[PDB]
Image (cartoon, rainbow, N blue to C red; front, side, top):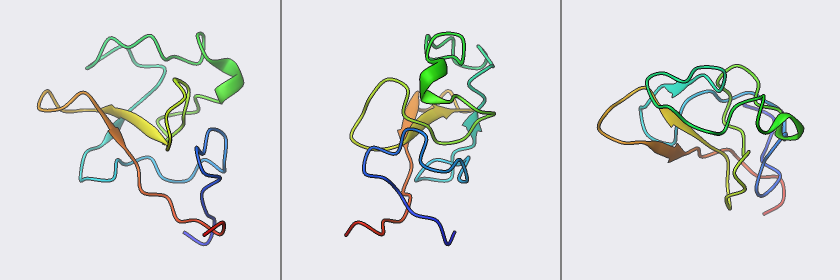
Length: 83
């Protein structure tokens, strides 16, 4: 990406849809695999678009739900112009 993170990166851009690890970000609109309460109906002002690494809950960094049963949610390593 040429775009970068806004620190907590809620609605930064909406590029990366994969965790920091090789986990596929499960869609925010999807209550499967993980039945999460962070949906675009719950956090619309956090822009839960598709499966992008958003920050609805309010972590230190963008995160998402993995399509794995191994792990629940995962952070995402977005770049940073604000180094």
